[PDB]
Image: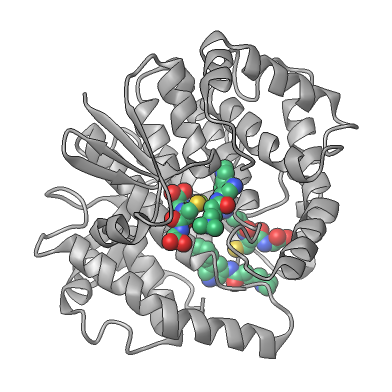
Length: 198
Length: 198
Ligand SMILES: CN(C)CCCC(=O)Nc1cncc(-c2cccc3[nH]ccc23)c1
Ligand SMILES: CN(C)CCCC(=O)Nc1cncc(-c2cccc3[nH]ccc23)c1
Ligand SMILES: N[C@@H](CCC(=O)N[C@@H](CS)C(=O)NCC(=O)O)C(=O)O
Ligand SMILES: N[C@@H](CCC(=O)N[C@@H](CS)C(=O)NCC(=O)O)C(=O)O
Ligand SMILES: [Mg+2]
């Protein structure tokens, strides 16, 4: 099966998919577009949003729907039906927060305001909830790595760009990040991927 | 299993779970709370949000994570892995849009203006995408009903409270609502359920 992933030249919402392809050792075309090219592609898409994944002439959309599809019947999914629910719940909780940021805001003063509010007021409480949820366990769900751990690592990486001191009082969440980053397939991708801010 | 759903006295984010329970003929306690008992329960919740589902003492959160868990290994989920991806993608698309509305805004004039803005520009754009995606086909995904159809009907029911003429130029989306509402288990629930605005 031939895979083509289309997104902007960033980690962003597409990176979870990039991690999953790397972990499962699946070859794919990593198509990165400029904003100048986007409107022409946008107009042809059913819902006009990216990332999209083309699989055998069939265009999938929604990053987490795609991530779930790719991890289905693999070791990145939950090991029980209930664990799969916990995986989906943690990912959605993270996705809910990341989606609050006005990534596409053109007015800089309004953008900086919102980022500062979310990072200063809201982010610390999410960290507290995540840290308590993890407890003293090795991974977020179950006894082995899932794509929820991937998603945590990806979200936290972007948050740390704007607020470097986010996990100062959360050593266990730092440990989880480093374990995800230590997985060979993930480590390899982290080193070779295009180095962008977001 | 012993199920207990906790949410406000409204359809809201919980209604998709209530539809699935009714369609699959699965018994559960539909616990509806007032504002008075929310702070007490909120403290016991790992992530401080509802709906939540308690399954034999084990708590679950995130409405769509719970919905997907309940539809596991049924035809409601989608027949193939690819269809299940389409189902997930449509639901997330609808959920993304419904999440844009300022449901908890206390400034009534601000709320009015933001609702009007979303219903005038964004809603019609999404409706055209949904309508063309459905085409002249019977259901949104595949040959039979999925919980994506349920979710469309639920979301559109709330949207029609604020803009009654939203689907007046989309007869195919009106037809889809009617088909879902006519499903015996859904028809029974819609008659039974408490009457609320949202
Ligand atoms: C052209 N520019 C204005 C558009 C670029 C959009 C952008 O910066 N996307 C972006 C950048 N960083 C994070 C997310 C994001 C949003 C929601 C959930 C997410 N999860 C991981 C990243 C992520 C999204
Ligand atoms: C005053 N406050 C305590 C009540 C706020 C509850 C409320 O109005 N929630 C609500 C009401 N109507 C729709 C949604 C909603 C939000 C996001 C995705 C959704 N999908 C279906 C409903 C829905 C949520
Ligand atoms: N919930 C969707 C959201 C996708 C989305 O909104 N993507 C943004 C970029 S991060 C986009 O397409 N922006 C360009 C546009 O809206 O025209 C997902 O996770 O895929
Ligand atoms: N993505 C979550 C969002 C849940 C959510 O935010 N629910 C609202 C009520 S509809 C809530 O509990 N808000 C927290 C609060 O204001 O106390 C889900 O779908 O379950
Ligand atoms: Mg979501």
